């Protein structure tokens, strides 16, 4: 539902390569993206099920 | 002239892959049961992979050993990225040979100008995406603190160093974190962070390993 849920996926500065989830509102579903390890924003979920539950339908 | 090059198989024998289903970071073997990596690489459910080249095929030189413990530095700061260091204990000791070897801890810090080797299976495009199969290397000089702190004003601590080329084009990137910066045989840095990758005026930022040598030696000794 929310408004962080519309914000684009933030990799940030750290050089990890960690696959996370974000709410893609242009697709209408939760997608994967490369999270660099630090300073995550809120549209950053550790599973699709969480993502769908917080953001799903935004 | 492209920054990284294909190191060669098992030519960087102390490189590890940290895996949790896929390769998420690097790390350095500092003795047969310990790995040093980046605190921001801390996950549950790591398997460390040793003796890799191609992380996607089983070339025969591998030892895949799960970790029993992961110790993040007591003062790691998630925001400021300060003290971005973690130690990882293997379930069981690695069998150490020619393709699988450890890297000595510094006995002093490297000066600006010192040329180092940065290895890792991170993204090989500055802008773009391409994750290699085999290990890539990069030789990149240590940067002066003064220049480092001009590149990232108000953000560099005593525990950090910049390395690379103000020109950009040659850097380390996403996938690279935790992996070594070896200088003159000794382990000096840990791949940590940056603004993008391989940008002009934005060198990579590394954990200054020679700051922690005491902490590591001891922490190893009593765990
Ligand atoms: Ca392999």
Image: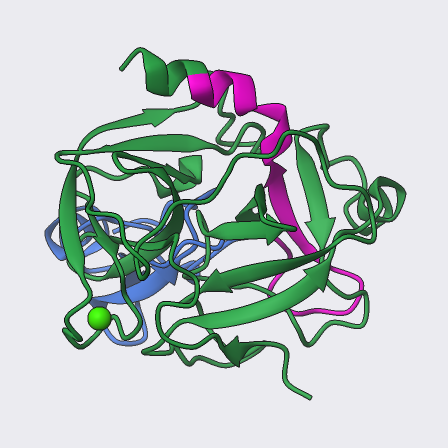
Chain colours: A blue, B green
Q: Is residue B193 visible?
A: no
Q: Residue at x 37, y 59 (%)?
A: A17
Q: Is residue B117 visible?
A: yes
- Answer whether residue A34 is magenta in the image: no
Q: Residue at x 59, y 60 (%)?
A: B117
* Quarter assignment of residue B221: top left
**Residue A7: image location, x then y, percent:** 43, 58
Question: As drawn, which residue projects farthest toward the top?
Answer: B222
**Residue A1: image location, x then y, percent:** 25, 51
Q: Nearer the viewer, residue B87 or B213?
A: B213
Question: As drawn, which residue projects farthest toward the front?
Answer: B97
Residue B119, placed above or below residue A26: above
Residue B59, placed above or below residue B27: below
| Numbered range of the magenta stretch | B193-217
Please state, as top left, top right, bottom left or bottom right, where the N terminus of chain B lies in the image. bottom right
Question: As drawn, which residue projects farthest toward the bottom?
Answer: B1
């Amino acid at each position: 539902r929310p408004d962080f849920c519309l914000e684009p996926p933030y990799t940030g500065p750290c050089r990890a390569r960690i696959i996370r989830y974000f709410y893609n509102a242009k697709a209408g579903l939760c997608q994967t993206f490369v999270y660099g390890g630090c300073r995550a924003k809120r549209n950053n979920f550790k599973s699709a099920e969480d993502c769908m539950r917080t953001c799903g339908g935004a | 002239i492209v920054g990284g090059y294909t190191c060669g198989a098992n030519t960087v024998p102390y490189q590890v892959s940290l895996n949790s289903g896929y390769h998420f970071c690097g790390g350095s073997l500092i003795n047969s049961q310990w790995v040093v990596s980046a605190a921001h690489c801390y996950k549950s459910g790591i398997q460390v992979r040793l003796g890799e080249d191609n992380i996607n095929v089983v070339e025969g030189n591998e030892q895949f050993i799960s970790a029993s413990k992961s110790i993040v530095h007591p003062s790691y700061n998630s925001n400021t990225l300060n003290n971005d260091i973690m130690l990882i204990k293997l379930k069981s000791a690695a069998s150490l040979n020619s393709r699988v070897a450890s890297i000595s801890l510094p006995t002093s810090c490297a000066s600006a100008g010192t040329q180092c080797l940065i290895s890792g299976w991170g993204n090989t495009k500055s802008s773009g995406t391409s994750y290699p199969d085999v290990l890539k290397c990069l030789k990149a000089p240590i940067l002066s603190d003064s220049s480092c702190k001009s590149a990232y004003p108000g953000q560099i601590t005593s525990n950090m160093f910049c390395a690379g080329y103000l020109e950009g084009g040659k850097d380390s990137c996403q996938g690279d974190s935790g992996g070594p910066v070896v200088c003159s045989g000794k382990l000096q840095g840990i791949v940590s962070w940056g603004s993008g990758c391989a940008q002009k005026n934005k060198p990579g930022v590394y954990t200054k390993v020679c700051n922690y040598v005491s902490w590591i030696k001891q922490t190893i000794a009593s765990n």
